[PDB]
Amino acid sequence: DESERGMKVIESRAQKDEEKMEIQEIQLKEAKHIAEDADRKYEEVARKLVIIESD
Amino acid sequence: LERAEERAELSEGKCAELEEELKTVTNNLKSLEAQAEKYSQKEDRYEEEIKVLSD
Image (cartoon, rainbow over all chains, first blue to last red; front, side, top):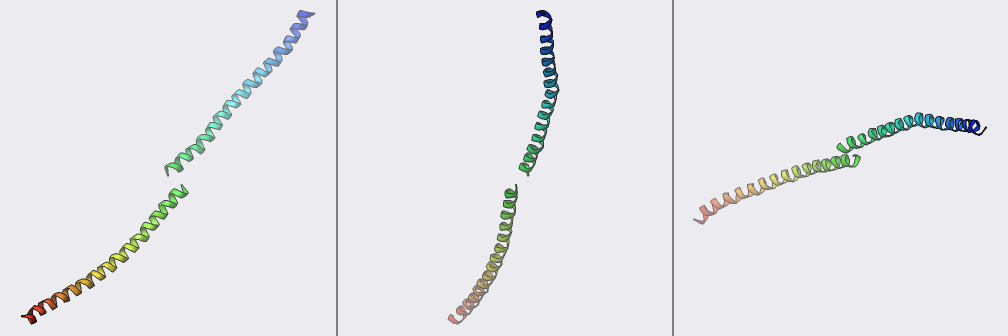
């Protein structure tokens, strides 16, 4: 019961951690894409700053 | 940029105003120079006549 409960607690934990893993991984890809977008919008506006600044 | 451009416009505007003020004083200078020269020419005509009458 303790090794099985353990296995089930761990399976539950493993699943919580697996979901958090996948959730954080999917959300990481999105956070990275937001960083790409955040850097992208930064570049669009910063580039405008440079263009406007160049002008 | 609006200010840099404003300054381009303001300094260009003003330099254009100065071109007009400059042409105005240049033309007034030319007029006064021509006038002063017409007088210097009259002074010379008189000087020639002064020399003629003095002699």
